[PDB]
Length: 100
Image (cartoon, rainbow, N blue to C red; front, side, top):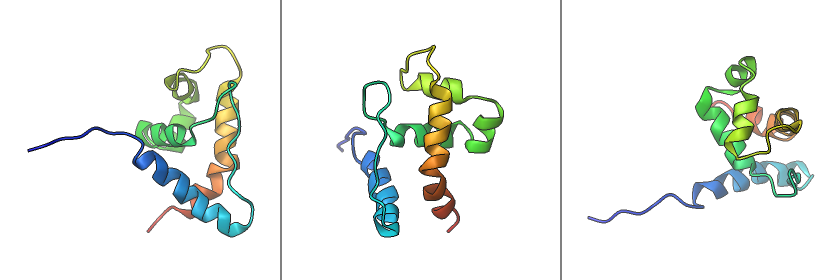
């Protein structure tokens, strides 16, 4: 019949999800500014999960590729930044939203 195309549908679910969790704790959900541009915590997390989880990509120091995926500047200490922001904000959001 008819078809569509992926857009900013789910990309929002991530924000509403991580938010609904933070807004509750007390501290509003804030996004860090990397590369003179807003960070898409949605893409980073998404990719990882796909790659093969956090422990996997982490063990294979794939962080490098995970960063370049978002068209990041190859040369700057980004890998570290990402891994951090994740375990910094995406740490509780995940561990909490893990296991139904």
